[PDB]
Image (spheres, coloured by chain):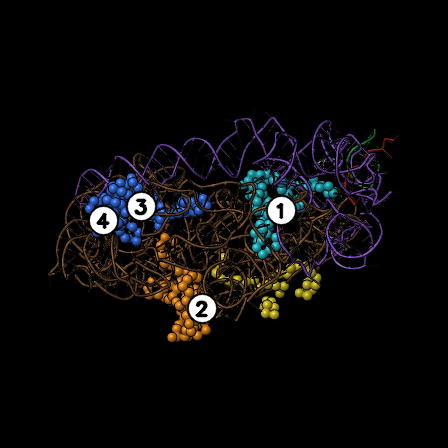
Chain colours: A blue, B yellow, C orange, D cyan, E green, F red, G brown, H purple
Amino acid sequence: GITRDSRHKRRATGGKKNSMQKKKKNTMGRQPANTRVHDVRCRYGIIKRRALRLENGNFSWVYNASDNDFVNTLVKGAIIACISSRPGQTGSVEGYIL
Amino acid sequence: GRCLRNHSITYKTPKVPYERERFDAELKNKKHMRTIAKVML
Amino acid sequence: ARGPRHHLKRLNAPHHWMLSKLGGTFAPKPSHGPHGMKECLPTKRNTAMMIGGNGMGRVGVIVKREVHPGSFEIVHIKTFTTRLNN
Amino acid sequence: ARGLHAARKMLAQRRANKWADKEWKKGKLVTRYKCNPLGTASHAKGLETKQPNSGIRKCVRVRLLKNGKKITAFVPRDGSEVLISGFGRRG
RNA sequence: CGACUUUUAAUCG
RNA sequence: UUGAAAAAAU
RNA sequence: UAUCUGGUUGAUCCUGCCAGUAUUAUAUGCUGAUGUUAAAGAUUAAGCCAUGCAUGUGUAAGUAUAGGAUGAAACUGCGGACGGCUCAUUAUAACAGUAAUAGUUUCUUUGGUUACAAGGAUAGCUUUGUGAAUGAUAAAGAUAAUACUUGAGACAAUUCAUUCAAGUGAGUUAGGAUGCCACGACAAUUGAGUAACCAAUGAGAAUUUCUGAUCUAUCAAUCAGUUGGUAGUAUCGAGGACUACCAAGAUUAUAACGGAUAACGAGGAAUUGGGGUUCGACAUCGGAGAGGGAGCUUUACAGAUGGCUACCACUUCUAAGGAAGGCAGCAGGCGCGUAAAUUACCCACUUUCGAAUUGAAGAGGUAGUGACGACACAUAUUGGAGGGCAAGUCUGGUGCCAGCAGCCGCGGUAAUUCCAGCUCCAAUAGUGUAUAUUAAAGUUGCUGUGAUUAAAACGCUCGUAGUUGAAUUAAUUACUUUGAAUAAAAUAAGAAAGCGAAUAUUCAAGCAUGGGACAAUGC
RNA sequence: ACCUUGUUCAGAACUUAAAGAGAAAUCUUGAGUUUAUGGACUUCAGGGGGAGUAUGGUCACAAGGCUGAAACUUAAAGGAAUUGUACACACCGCCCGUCGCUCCUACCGAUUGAAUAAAGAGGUGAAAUUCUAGGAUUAAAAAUGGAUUUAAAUCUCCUUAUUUAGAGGAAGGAGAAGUCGUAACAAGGUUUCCGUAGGUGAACCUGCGGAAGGAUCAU
Ligand SMILES: NC[C@@H]1O[C@H](O[C@H]2[C@@H](O)[C@H](O[C@@H]3[C@@H](O)[C@H](N)C[C@H](N)[C@H]3O[C@H]3O[C@H](CO)[C@@H](O)[C@H](O)[C@H]3N)O[C@@H]2CO)[C@H](N)[C@@H](O)[C@@H]1O
């Protein structure tokens, strides 16, 4: 479904690119499972730990810089302490005390 | 291309079809290095 | 290509394998291992040895080694010049 | 222009002047695909003289299978689906 | 139909 | 002062 | 071979074109003794397909009461993501060369490291069946694993926060240390097999840097995820690839945006004195596609279609309830058209895949058709006889009629041109005709054209972009010389052929280098 | 100062040439220094017609101007020379335009003229997926519901190419001997031609202004 190639974008001059092929699997995108833990079989057989939702979290010693709407999704750099891991990729929430 | 095997032509017909000074001189049937010499000279 | 290639064409085979152009449509594909496809075989192409460019097959001793931080470095041998990897 | 850096104009100048060529233009603009009864093809299957010569030229009218246009065609010899292939002069 | 002209074209009965 | 035309090819 | 000839006039000298000529590849008319080599449904319809084959695979080393080795089937494993076909797409896209990946990375292979055995069920096996049937499926009862698990002999790599810090042109970099999380073994394997990690294979795959494409102004302004910034998401991974906020930015006369192609690109081919013009679907490299889109599965690799799902459009079987299929694989049929071969045999060459020395392969080889072409080679045709252009001022008819003639023209009754008969002219197993490429064409002009009168100096001046710009002096770029590096085939080169040439290319870019005369950019 | 002489510039010209150039007429203060081919730059041309016509675009109140094809047709058209000559069958020459008769080609096209194949915004929306709920069956897990994502297919207006169209037409071209005139070539019997305006069966005629390609290089 979601592709990540630049065959559908325009040029620096504003030109519209013309199709010469179809969507190829190497440009796969995936639906962003927002972390409000699953596993995804990525390319080359490695596994991605998709944390659908999660509440506990390791930390070491209320605001989203990107989208205020996210304020209770869990993303990197979110303030709750500031999350430092990628929960949607690694599958766990690791953060640090501000 | 069409074939891997090579081929060549072993003759070339003259430019002018009918010239008497050639019909007599040439008379089973009527079927390189000079320039190579030239290029080094 | 959907995946890694397996067959090999006679023409596409490396030159120094000395394969003819009419023996057969295909050439033996070298398996992966300690040596590359174009650096192995399944002057006719300290003292050193040239394995790479035009100097392949030449033995001799180095005089000096210019270095260019941009791209590469050059080795001069008793004289002919070539890159380090050769 | 003749200078060493004026390669843009002479390249541009030649492209413009080529269109004046009657023979060259006929082979590039779109008439060999819509105005030529033969198209680009050699043959085509289908179904009184000038002032100082007197007589009658026997001829034939032919409707082409593909295009459908009607053309006038000569008969080859004395006392002589049809295949038609041009004449000595091209077009 | 013929006559006319190098032929014809017409014309003339 | 008025003064137009000469059937087709050899 | 750096080559021309006929035609405007009573005659001349021009401009200028038509025609003549040679050649390459398509078709086609007539004709055909051999040997060798060899193209062959691309153009028109990536239009439709009847039928048959094109992908299966077994060793001592997985599981076998269908215990001697052997052993079909089945489970399990591997592959069918390579190979083969086609050129519909596509105009800086793809492709070629060059550079990077300190921005990603498997599969295979190769090197290295890190409880005397436990638990259950399952196919083939047997039993019942079902519908017309698909490569159709339902019930029941057993039995194994290198199938699936648990379990121990004791680490490896992920995330996070802090810190010590040597290669490389260049890294808070490889790496070490601290605490945390995650994951967690070297089959409870078989007569070789296995997990995690590191490296190579790997110059490889994939993204990406620079330079390079045909015609068009009767296409002049174009772009709003558009151009950038922050932060996240998603990805194998960089990045507006995407989401939220912020900014107004990006391209263009050095041709942007848009349009056309009877456009897949390159290596190459045809022809050329030099310079160039035209072609390149088609051997090999890269790209894209499987009737049209789209969405997915499995895996290490697919947006796979000789895999699936839905819609559109078709094809087929049907017992009428239902059911499958995708020839642009090999043969072969239709349709189309001027235009293109056998419904052959075999894995014996080359090579690939497989549990592997065996099996399989319409890949591949062999055989068949095959004046596409090419080389050598018997002894008979094709066109022509006014000129161009070699060849009769021979004989019969026809009478501006039939006709011939690529052009000049010949024929109006005594034809060197018609239709015949004879003879000789060119080439010859070939030779006519039509179409198109190239040369001729100095009739497209850089080398190289012309512009008083033959076609052709804007009515005139100003003026932006462009181009071109006097002499003079003891940092880049351009230029120039050498190298490096540079797929083969082909070209040329050391009967057509075939097989190690230093074989040299092969330009446009890019890298290194000696020089600074002629140049451009600011100092 | 005005007139007469010399010297050196700028300007409009003229005379000779055994030279240079050209096809020649002629040019010479270039139309010379060009196959012994390159001083700098801009514009234009590619046999004759169809044609400066059609379509499209744009400027003007309009007449019109600027940009500007193709189909098709044809072996010549043209230049300079052997008092003017477009004549050489040689003026009993050549030739122009309208009309009459056949055939062909493109263009327009009341007939709301259409029709077909391909491109953007809005509506309907299969299917498969991500998530969620459910858990028949034996923690696993099937039917099924719901919300996203990707979106085929279809409908509505709009953007490119290919086709059918009759009254209504309107042009051009080709074919020995068909009509009406005398327009042009001699001073062609009113010198000719260009622009423009008007009239006219037709060539054309007349007004204003140019040009000699004039029948005058001259008082
Ligand atoms: N070419 C188109 C124009 O034709 C116009 O006119 C055309 C006709 O009106 C003119 O006709 C001539 C006529 O003038 C003359 N006085 C008599 C002659 N028989 C006609 O002749 C014409 O028509 C006849 C009809 O049978 C045809 O056979 C003949 O071939 C043709 N030339 O001949 C011309 C060709 O058809 C102008 N004359 C001409 O200038 C213009 O170019």
Query: Distance of mark 1 from mark 2, alpha carbons?
Result: 52 Å
Q: Which quarter of the picture shows residue B14?
A: bottom right
Give the class, few, some or many, for how many residues have Cα within 10 Å of label 1's Cα (few <14, many ≥20). few
Q: Which quarter of the picture shows residue D62?
A: top right
Q: Chain of mark 1?
A: D
**Coordinates of residue D46 in the picture (x, y in percent):** 57, 41
Give the labeled residue for mark 4.
A97
- Residue A52 visible in the picture: no
* Viewer-closest of C64 and B22: C64
Q: Is residue H135 left or right of residue H113?
A: left
**Coordinates of residue D50 in the picture (x, y in percent):** 71, 41
Residue at x-position 28% and y-position 47%: A77
Amino acid type, callout 4: Ile
Residue at x-position 57% and y-position 55%: D5
Give the labeled residue for mark 1.
D20
* Viewer-closest of A89 and G130: A89
Q: Chain of mark 2?
A: C
Give the labeled residue for mark 2.
C54
What is the secondary structure assignment of the residue under circle 1? loop
**Coordinates of residue G243 in the picture (x, y in percent):** 34, 41
Q: Chain of mark 3?
A: A
Give the labeled residue for mark 3.
A30
